[PDB]
Amino acid sequence: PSKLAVAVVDSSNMNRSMEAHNFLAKKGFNVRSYGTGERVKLPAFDKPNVYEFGTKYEDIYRDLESKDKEFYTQNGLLHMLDRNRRIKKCPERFQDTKEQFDIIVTVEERVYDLVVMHMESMESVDNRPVHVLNVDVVNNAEDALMGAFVITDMINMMAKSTDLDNDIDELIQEFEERRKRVILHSVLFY
Amino acid sequence: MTDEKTATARAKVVDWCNELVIASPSTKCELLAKVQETVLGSCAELAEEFLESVLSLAHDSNMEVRKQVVAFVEQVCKVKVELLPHVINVVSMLLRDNSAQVIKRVIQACGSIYKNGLQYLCSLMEPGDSAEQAWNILSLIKAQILDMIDNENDGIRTNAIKFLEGVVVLQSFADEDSLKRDGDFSLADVPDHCTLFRREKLQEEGNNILDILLQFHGTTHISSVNLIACTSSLCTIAKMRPIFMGAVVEAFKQLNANLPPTLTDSQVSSVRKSLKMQLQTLLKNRGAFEFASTIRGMLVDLGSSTNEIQKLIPKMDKQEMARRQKRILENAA
Image (cartoon, rainbow over all chains, first blue to last red; front, side, top):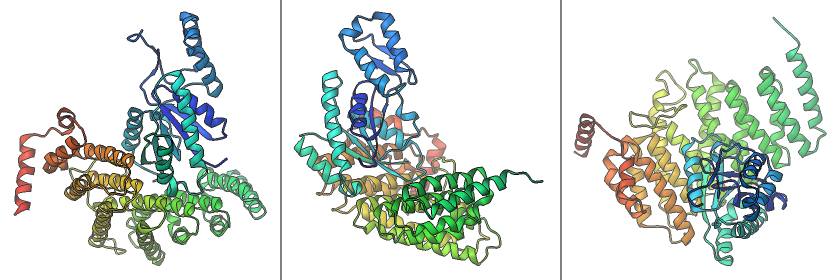
């Protein structure tokens, strides 16, 4: 409805960012998503499924298919890869993008730190501020879905504001209260 | 030697400038985007004659249009900075704008505009009257934006703080301990042949803006966003100009001991996490040598381990330390 450029950021750019990306896009928002990790990591505990950022979601689908089509059908990972391939081609890395946002939402504190470190590491040119918010989302299928509803709810509330900068601290404060959550909120510059 | 390129480009923008007076504000922004990519990009020569066409749209009722004018004028000072006196008036005028969205965008653009404008004016050997006029508007822009730290809008205040950061950095001297930054410009880069202003007066202003930022940073009713922005701006200033390091470290020390009671528990965590990062950055600067133990004290208060802090301190040779240790002893007397 409103002209907010939003980004959702996680480790992977696979589960939690894509659940939120999906729901925000369906609400009509100019949304993009990214991962803060070095490489794309999917689920033995010491044996994960690793791929590069820039790898098509479809290539990851065919790789896990030919490895073991049955295991990744039972854990619903192929269902996730389905959703993501419909949203965009390949998962992207936040640290490499030249896109600018009004709001950035991270799904855990460790991601938040990564985003903030990165943004700060780059000298500001446009002098344009951006709000970085952290909403904790526990990394599993069920909680990534519930989390994506919260993030959507939070961005909807923020989209309603006629002056976001001037109202955002009050909005967060009362949102935190009503939803019994802690939203870390910082400001960074492009 | 000639060709068709200029004439073919002029015919394209004449068409676009004619559509503007009868176009909807949404169509006006599309048209202006195309006119800027041509007139400041593909065929840069077309700048001077289509200037007034674009600058007239600074009076348009739609704020998006007004914001596009700012975007254009900011580009003009980047690629055709010789046109600076012919555009700078609209910028000072747009700082009196009614829409906060326009004010914020103008302050943002004034960062590059003031740097590019200051670089160009002190480069001129025989500066004219138009150069004195442009400098006077730049002086007023600084004062205008400086007043906006007491604006009622939080977003305006944030942008104003960020603008003031670049001014302090420009209007101070770099040294050996300054962070290596590509386009870095200091009062050392301002020539003695320049009549337009004096290095001492700019330094005096830079020191006054810093004093204002240091005081602002220490108030009890500051917003969490303004506080975070101010803290990071103070960090940029100290790492760029380590002469201000002691003052910034003291401000940080005072803040961590007296967090404004207007901050929420979340805001405190947010402020402290940002403060931690700024302190870590400053500890990497060679100019922080004298304040290494103070900074360590605060980082320990903010949860850093002994080994995390230790890894940040730059390695120095003993002769370098002795130079510094003895400079610190002579300055104390």
